[PDB]
Image: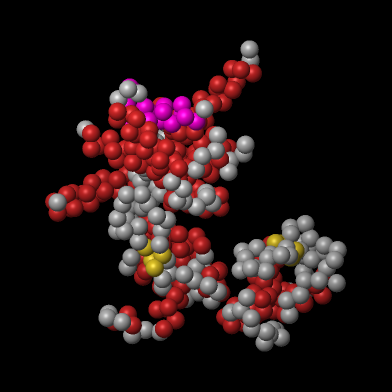
Amino acid sequence: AAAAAANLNAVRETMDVLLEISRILNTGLDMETLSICVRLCEQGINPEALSSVIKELRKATEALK
Amino acid sequence: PVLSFLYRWIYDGELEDTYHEFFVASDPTVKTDRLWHDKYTLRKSMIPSFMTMDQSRKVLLIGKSINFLHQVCHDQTPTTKTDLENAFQGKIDAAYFETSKYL
Amino acid sequence: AQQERDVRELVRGVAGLQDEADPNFQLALNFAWSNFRFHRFLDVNSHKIEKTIEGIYEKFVIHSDLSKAASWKRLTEEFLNADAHYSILSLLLCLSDSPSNSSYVE
Amino acid sequence: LECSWDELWNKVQQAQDLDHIIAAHEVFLDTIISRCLLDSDSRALLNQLRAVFDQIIELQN
Amino acid sequence: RATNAQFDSPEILRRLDVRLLEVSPGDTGWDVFSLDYHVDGPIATVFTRECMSHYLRVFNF
């Protein structure tokens, strides 16, 4: 109806905003990967472990290329 | 009583008025080094008509400076010495010269 | 349940391995869960995250990027009103980082 | 850094009052930013100066 | 002690301190290193917080 369409706008705003914060830092993420990471830390996960996961998945993708 | 409010604010550095009569209005809770930047406002409604703005500025400039000498400089050795028959501009420039040069 | 699918989608997204029948997918996933379960960090300090956010704002006002400073403050102040927050911020902060470049995107 | 210091030194030393020492010191501080390339208007001149500062270490490599 | 800066009053030699910036990701210390000279007292009325931030912008260049 209407309240199911306002939440999509309020989510698209914040998902543009987090991409802004991501590239003012110069994180290597893009719009697709950040939506996975944001979803993961919504449920409650140690970001210091999730960061090390990404920091070595990107470290092991280079030995294969 | 206006001149008695003027005689202790400039020579000893006292602003005692529970009812807001003197045109300098102390703001409390400025215990830090914002004593020069804050804590003294020239209230324009209680400046009497027989004082122009520049005399009302210099009386605040002396009265803050003796209080600055006591509160921040920690040097308490003061006793620091027709509108009202043209002795405003006489004594105030002397008090401005003695205190600010000692400051 | 949703967590396992999220980690699989994370492996697919970051590592570019869209086939689960690739052995490299399962090696990346096994690593991801093993790194997840190797608890070796302190928990997130909310105050240190707030200090870092404020310092990023100070770096923007120092470099006279006024639109980016006002942006950064507006977005961090909006996001921090309704623990998990500081987790996202610390995540993005360490994730890669480290260029002062344009990023208006306003 | 030098005539601005020369502008600062004579204006501070002559004053009788602590308010002229504070107000002329900020003039010394503000004229440094404008005679340098750290201003908001002279930042685009600094951004081209970044590339020559890039070319020095580029020649080093 | 190696330069002639040690031949000065020990007050102003003590007040200058290395300031660490906040730590950057992958970078060198040449981009993050600056002196702070820290000031505490009646001198802070002349050398306010606005002065030291603008001095640090000068040291940045």
Percent from the top left, x then y, of residue B89?
68, 74
Q: Is residue D59 left or right of residue C97?
A: left
Q: Nearer the viewer, residue A23 or C15?
A: C15
Q: Is residue C52 above or below residue B17?
A: above
Q: Is residue B82 above or below residue C77?
A: below
Percent from the top left, x then y, of residue E17?
41, 71
- Chosen colour scheme: secondary structure
Q: Is residue A14 above or below residue E25?
A: above
Q: Is residue C39 left or right of residue C24?
A: right
Percent from the top left, x then y, of residue C55?
48, 52
Percent from the top left, x then y, of residue D25?
46, 66
Q: Nearer the viewer, residue E43 or D34?
A: E43
How many numbered markers are drawn?
A: 0
> Magenta-highlighted stretch: main secondary structure?
helix
Q: Nearer the viewer, residue C92 or A55?
A: A55
Q: Is residue C59 above or below residue A36?
A: below
Residue at 73%, 76% in the rendered image: B13
Quadrant housing the C terminus of chain E: bottom left
Residue E30 among magenta residues: no
Quadrant housing the N terminus of chain E: bottom left
Does the rendering let one see residue B90? Answer: no
Residue at 72%, 74% in the rendered image: B88
Residue at 32%, 68% in the rendered image: D2
Residue at 49%, 33% in the rendered image: A40
Residue C8 among magenta residues: yes
Residue B7 found in image quarter: bottom right
Residue most extreme to the top:
A1
Task: Please give the range of residues in magenta.
Answer: C3-19
Does the rendering let one see residue B9? Answer: yes
